[PDB]
Image (cartoon, rainbow, N blue to C red; front, side, top):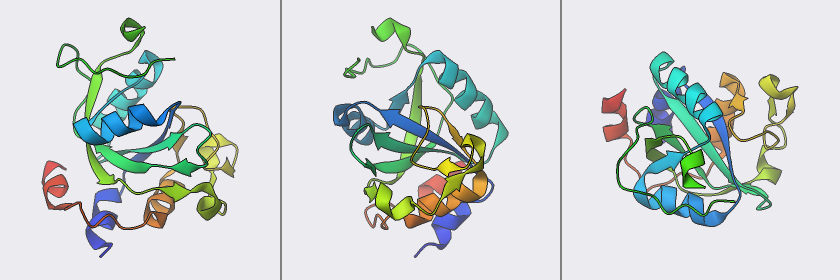
Length: 161
């Protein structure tokens, strides 16, 4: 292991990402991309310039779980290869962020019930709107709860910091 993981998470910022379907998280895991509404796009871009690592923690609505977490590797950009998200229009979305997955394993909410987010009224960290920032200590402990993803090598992520 957890040492490189702790290094990547040192002084990071964390954001809760809530997807309404599994297809979008699967696309993000396969293509290394995410897109969000402009209100959150602006917050993530500010965060990306402000911190060594910005971590997105993903949860599919109604799943009772987180599906993993990833680190922003770019600010949002437009153009690019289109992404066939399952939308609840594509013009309403902001740009596309490139992301590097740190863990593609799931974590059930039952395992994070002891973690509260000060930036959301100390409600359990599972609770929050899409884009809710997670305070540093809560976010770090939440990431450390995930099962280790032995498919990922954090060596290349570290070099991007």
